[PDB]
Structure formats: C-alpha cells, structure tokens
Amino acid sequence: AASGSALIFDEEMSRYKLLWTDPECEIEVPERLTVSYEALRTHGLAQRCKAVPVRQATEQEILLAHSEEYLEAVKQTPGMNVEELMAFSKKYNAVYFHQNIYHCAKLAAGATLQLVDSVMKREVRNGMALVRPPGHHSQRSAANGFCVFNNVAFAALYAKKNYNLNRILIVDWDVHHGQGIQYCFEEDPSVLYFSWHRYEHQSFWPNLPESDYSSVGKGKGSGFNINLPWNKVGMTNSDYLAAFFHVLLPVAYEFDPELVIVSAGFDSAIGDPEGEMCALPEIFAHLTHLLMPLAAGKMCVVLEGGYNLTSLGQSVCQTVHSLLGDPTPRISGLGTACDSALESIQNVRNVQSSYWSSFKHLAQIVWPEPLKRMPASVRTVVVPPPGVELTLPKNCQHSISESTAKEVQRIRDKHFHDLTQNILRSLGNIISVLDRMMRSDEVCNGCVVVSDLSVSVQCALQHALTEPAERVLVVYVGDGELPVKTNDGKVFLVQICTKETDKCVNRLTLCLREGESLTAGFMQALLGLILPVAYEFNPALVLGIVEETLMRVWGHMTCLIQGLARGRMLTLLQGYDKDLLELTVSALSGASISPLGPRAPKPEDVEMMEKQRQRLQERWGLLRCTVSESW
Ligand SMILES: CN(C)CCc1cn(Cc2ccc(C(=O)NO)cc2)c2ccccc12
Ligand SMILES: [K+]
Ligand SMILES: [K+]
Ligand SMILES: [Zn+2]
Image 1 (spheres, rainbow, N blue to C red):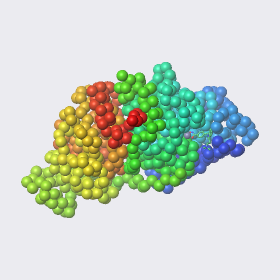
Image 2: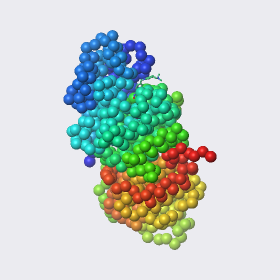
Image 3: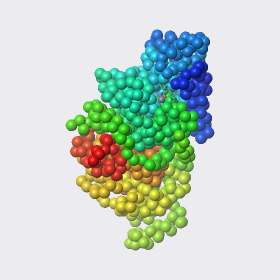
Image 4: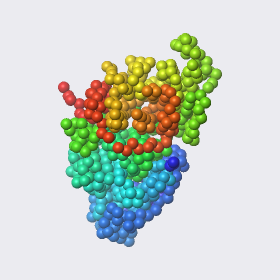
C-alpha cells in the first residue's frame, strides 16, 4: 500500500566548508549539495517527492556506531577556532572540521534515520537523502575521508534495533571503499555489505589490504562482506552491469533482504576527477532499478561522494527518476566487461563460492546530456476477455479505431484468408495498444489476453517491427514453436520451455527441470543469462508471451525486464487466469513486488545454464564472468 518517494534535504548541511589550504580536501564543497537539489528542482523531480524534514541524530543514536570518546571529542569542535580545528583535523586522514560540521553531521545522520523511518513505516515506498558530510569512511572512533559519522551504518543499526530486521543489504556504489561500513558489520551476517571501488592493486586511497576481494568478513559474518576492486580506471556501463549481473544481484536475491540501503556516491560516474571511471549518469537509473524488486521496494538511497558538479546533478536525477518509477533510459553500446573487470569479477566469485549458491557450482570529460524521462500519461493498458471488469490501479486503463479496424482487415485478407473467432478483436487490441506505446508516447506498456497464439504473436511481432521497432526482444513461456524469425538480427528469442531443445546465437532456450527448485533456477537464469543478453541486445520493445500450459517468478521478470526498451513491454497471456493477469498488470504498472524469500537449484539446471553461457558469450560478451582464454 506504500506509495511515493521521500526526498530529505536541508540547506543547513551546505553551511560548513574547508577553511584552510588542503588540496586533498578542497574538492568537498557545499555546492555539491546545492547543485544536486537544484538539478532535482529543474527537472521537476523534487516537486514530485515527499519532503521529509531533517532532524538531529540523538547522542544515544550516535552511540549505536561510535564510541563515547570519539563523540565527546567531535562535540568540542563547535567551540574551536581555525587553528584548533586544523590541529584537530590532522589527527585523522583526509578530513577537515568546521565550527558547524558537528551540527551538520548530526543532521546528515538524522536525515538518514528520517528516511529509514518513513520507508519502514510505509509512509513512502523509497527515498533519497541529500546529505553532507558523507558517512561511509567514518569509523567507531575516527573521522576519515570527509566523513564524521557513518550515516549508512547508523541506518542499518537503527533499522535492526527499532524494526527488528534480520537481513539488511547495503550497496556501496561510491568509487571509494566504504571501509567504515565494512569494519562495522565485519562479523555481522544480518547486514550484507557490497562495495565496488577504485583499488588499482591497493595503490588507490584508502590503500587497504582489506578492500580486496579476499575480505569476505569474519566469524559468523564470513561471506557477508563482498568487495569488488577496480584495478584500472575507465570502467564503463558494461563493467558496472557485469558486476551487478554476475556478483551483486545473484547474492542479493538469495539473501532476500528486508531493507536495502544504498551508499550512493556518484564519483563513480564519468567526468568525476576522483573516480576517473566512464559510466554514464544513465547507468544509475538501472543500478537503482535492478535493486527495486528487493525488499518490496523498500530502498533508502543516501548520498556519499561525487565531485564533478555537472556529472553530479545528472546522476542524482537518474536515481530519483527510477525511485519515482519513471521509465529507464536505453543503454546502447554494451558488451563484454574489460579484462581487468573480469579478473576482479572472477576472483570475487571464486572466493565467495563457498558461501553463495549461485557461485557454488565452480568450487567442484565531456558526455552527451541524458534524455528526458517523462512518465507515460497512463502507464499500463489492460485488455481482459470480453466482458471482464477488474479492479485496476490508478495508473492503468482498459483498451478500437476505424483506421485500426481497416488494418486488421488488410492483415486477414493477406495472411489468414480463412479466419473469422473474436480473435479479430484481440488483433485490433494488440495494434491499438502498440500504437499508443510506440508512437503516441501516451501509454508505456500493456497486457492483452488472447485465444489463438500464432495469429496474435505473428501480428504483434510484425506490427511492432514497422512501428518502427529496430529490435524486438521476445520472452516466451511455453514448449511450442512460434512464428518468430531470428535470422536478421532484429529479434532475439528467450524461451522458457519444458521440452529439451537451439543452434544459433539469437535464441536462448531454457529447459528447467520441473520441481521445487524451479524458482531458484529461473532467478539464476534471469540475472545471469537473460538480463545480460537483453541489455546488450538493447531492444526497442519487449514481447512477453505465456501459453496456457509454476510462475511465482513472473512478477520479478516483468519488473526487471522493464529496464529494456524504455519499459515498453507488451505481454500476451493465452487464456484467462485472474491471478496471473493481476500480477502481470501489477508489475507492469510499477507496483512493488512481493519478495521470493527462500531452495537451491538443481545442478542439471546449473550445468544447462552454463552450457548456454559457453555457447552464447562469444557473441554476447556481457554474459562473461571470467577472463577470456587467449589462443
Ligand atoms: C586531486 N584528486 C585527483 C585527488 C585528491 C585527493 C583526495 N583525497 C581524499 C578523498 C577522500 C574521500 C573521497 C570520497 O569520495 N569518499 O567517498 C574522495 C577523496 C585523497 C587521498 C589521497 C591522495 C589524494 C587525494
Ligand atoms: K564503494
Ligand atoms: K557484514
Ligand atoms: Zn567516494
């Protein structure tokens, strides 16, 4: 029932700054905050957010994660002059203090707690806090790397204590390692910490052996710390998405968190003078979107770093766009991760393979401005069988024009001479829905219930190609063979079937053993095969097809597959099924997805899937999770 996105912000956190010469520190400026909020305002996103106010973290709250001694020290800095503040600043690494920073640090922390409470109370679905100072470097008794108190560590400790959560996921996509967070939960299996970071074989700050992939946690916490070191600069969209598909997401969906907190540093985006990576701001729309099916969408995004004032606003906007449910922008030019990324990916997977099921099987600048992302007028159109009313969410709608009807006549009087049930109606619905999706910019996606599969599939696919749709991704659940030509490179077919068998690289056929393991195997294939191929293909439309002949998984796929084609997906359900039609519509409309919870996949399925990767990854490089064997 939760709706809306929170945006926690306050101009007071911009009212402390660096007061002496320090080339390391001078990058951390108030304008980082003012530029990010103003960019949200300009694109109309802040106005669409629930503005929860900041508060101070209390002393007892600060003590959840920091020592009394350290608090008492920081608590004296408001009374210090500049010389005393400089002298106190030098007790720590890469951090400066100011007369007002203790105030601002309590506000940065309290804002984070406000965001946790609004999400966990169901007052909003998700949200973002724009805070200074950042948090993820700060430690139990030390300020570090512009950080005073550990905002995101607070949040998970506070969520644990006050909502009795057993499993919290922290995703730290800042370009620096959040070592403060690692230490905090080093031994804690209830908080899973994932971080990627510029490492360069430990030569990049903070220069820690424990930022490497071999730090999997300690004690009961082994396997709940996941470090992915970047050992070269210039990482791209493809490296970031490879990290999610082949490390983070497989673990995240098996973990099944009850809350997601994001250390959202954007110094990992192109143009940042500190990260020196090359991922576009648009990628953050997808990093955000790929995590939203977790924890019924309960996601708290907390600003960490980001220093190119221009790159910064754009990446903040893409994140909030996705939190609000706006359609994701198309990512073009995707392919294999670079060799350094695949080495890091391969290494982290191997060492984590003793702890996680998905990996367990191999223990045996200038850039173009992002487009506009307006949500469609109505998001989802539904076409149930004739004379079936259904309770539809507020952003959905039922379906047939004269021109449209003339076209159905032309298609019958050419390709189906002898056809006369109410199929002609479904064909007119397919065409009119597609026309509103592709050309009209009015609706986003839709679902139509159909009788005859061949004529509707053929006519949906063919009509989509001439919209025009450069490329069409087809996802079909059924053991038949469809009127789909995968020979010109304009179509890629994914088939989830029961029969045993493909011989070309434009079809992925998944024959999952029937049983209780069907759900884990499906999610394994979704994250590690279907999504990487689909993202590289970069379709202009997704065509989902379900034949009337075990799909507690369909909602997740519908949700994740809307990362492609700007969310333009048309689903054909053969035969009426109230439940499946309602779940399809609900996921299509942007509703939150119910968690899967917990049963490991059959090795027959794992072996079947790895044969598919071996067969496809030379053509679709985003499938790779090992370095290529060189001849
Ligand atoms: C001029 N540039 C190229 C480097 C200047 C420079 C900043 N720091 C500190 C620092 C701390 C935290 C974050 C962050 O974003 N955390 O999330 C970013 C930087 C250094 C440390 C060691 C050597 C150089 C530097
Ligand atoms: K990080
Ligand atoms: K941990
Ligand atoms: Zn950083």
